[PDB]
Image (cartoon, rainbow over all chains, first blue to last red):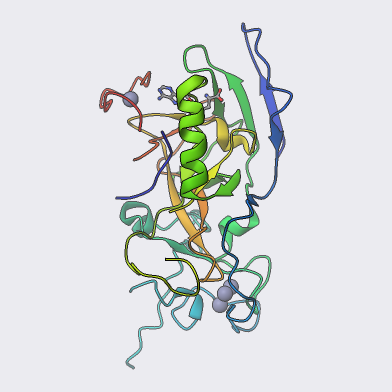
Length: 7
Length: 266
Ligand SMILES: Nc1ncnc2c1ncn2[C@@H]1O[C@H](CSCC[C@H](N)C(=O)O)[C@@H](O)[C@H]1O
Ligand SMILES: [Zn+2]
Ligand SMILES: [Zn+2]
Ligand SMILES: [Zn+2]
Ligand SMILES: [Zn+2]
């Protein structure tokens, strides 16, 4: 997978 | 501000191929807007870049105016230079200054810019492999370090994600620069979503383990204002942290003790 930043 | 590695009881060591870098590195198929539309602030101074007069915080909304302070960091308490609580809880991008403004090194709104100010120590936990802990206290709101690596595009990533996720190592190290998406748507210029990968090049934060009740969180730090599709990834302490406690953060926001454990990661 991958690291993220959303909300 | 030295990195130290410690491994008690394992025979593992850092791969001789891994490399430590101070600044991220762009891959070749990624964007670099013209130095022709770059804007910093003329302030004189120182600054006095803590008030709305500075063009660096336009997008930052408010015998008659206021003529109040607004730059997302505290200006004078024992918490000076620490992330405002308004920004912690509210997770709005941090608009910081850069090499385009008429302000210098201490410009109160250039924290992430200055880089890490606390010494870190990688140590070998037992279950989750390597992990990170700090040899000195870290008050909540504090800036630990930022996530680095090699900036790339969604397609080339798709390339590695599967080429890897299929035949070998699962250890994922790709962070997506998506605060703005988606727104625007358409275409413008031329053409009608590119990422940062630090498997073979990165900073200490490359070793922080995921948790479901993290003591740290990541925020986007923006500068040029054209350089925002490739925004910095800042790791801020969301709560006070004793020494020797393993830095953690939710990879999206599993062997984590966390009673609130969301099942798995990602
Ligand atoms: N909460 C968690 N649960 C399971 N695996 C985790 C985890 N946090 C980190 N990892 C591991 O770490 C990888 C991402 S990067 C973490 C660095 C790793 N500890 C190292 O020694 O290089 C994940 O793919 C997984 O293999
Ligand atoms: Zn400034
Ligand atoms: Zn300014
Ligand atoms: Zn500025
Ligand atoms: Zn968990």
